[PDB]
Length: 385
Ligand SMILES: CN1CCC2(CC1)c1ccccc1N(Cc1ccc(C(=O)NO)s1)[C@H]2c1ccc(Cl)cc1
Ligand SMILES: [K+]
Ligand SMILES: [K+]
Ligand SMILES: [Zn+2]
Image (cartoon, helix red, strand yellow):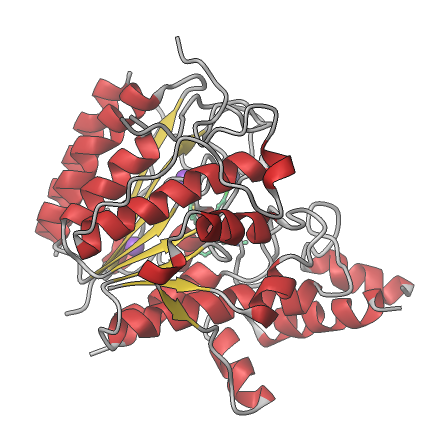
């Protein structure tokens, strides 16, 4: 059984941000055009009985002041003083993470979806749950970052590890380092975080690499030491090299940690067609690195959460996440989901030009040391625990 988060309210909220616009609509509608919805259980966003119940849930990670400020920001944008500016600036609610009429409703909705997905996994209603509206891994306890205002991921994991020793393995496939999720669990050995990403001088967010005798690689602290794994890669990596880099690490993490739940952030800014143009991954299937990683994770047969994330080429993002959904249906339910190479006709068909194919329009054409480092860390982590 495979679940997917969507709904009327969820849709408009997820499409109300200025940075991602209608991206969520394209994803859900392409999946729908391919007749996959009949194979998926809808997971309705989580709702609360009172504003106080909502606050306690969101303040499980964020501070009351920050949540307060995010709430006020929406109010002000729905119609600013000098003191307000200093207040907003103190939470980074400016510049990269500005406000808009629905800034709070938009951020909370992601939390609503990811929390519902975790409960769907906890009560065993679904073996895997997808949420293309979540995955905002940059949100910090009291700080917005990289257009991430509330960390739906952290709250979801908290719910998972809180349920009836539970250990959760977090895999971050986004092009950017998943700093927010990593810092939240810096001190906890019960949540092992693994992020593969690009890193270089001046590149956002700057973390997930060496620190500065010689450089050192931080990996948690306290009881959580050796619990934060990072693999930074240089620009230009292809599907093969990427899968080869993360492959053995993924296997070894599942073997050593034996997770009770796996949370996968599947941000789509690694595609060769993303505006960043850093990695050269595709969405191909005869092979895409994304699908190779999801297939390997699903093979573990562990209750898994699949989240969205970055991705500013909206059509190609939907192109990738549609195949992830189909592949998930194949692995979990055992029913092959042969997809049509041709994009099917639907409301957003125009946006998929000029070729209107499911494959992204791209023609493709060191890590060894990191493996030894990461293996040593895994041995240090296994022993420590
Ligand atoms: C503002 N607030 C101050 C406290 C700090 C960041 C946020 C924090 C809050 C909660 C848990 C941990 C941590 N930090 C320790 C680290 C976490 C990941 C690291 C890495 O290097 N990953 O690759 S270091 C601090 C930090 C994080 C990043 C930087 Cl650049 C500087 C300081
Ligand atoms: K990442
Ligand atoms: K950890
Ligand atoms: Zn990203």
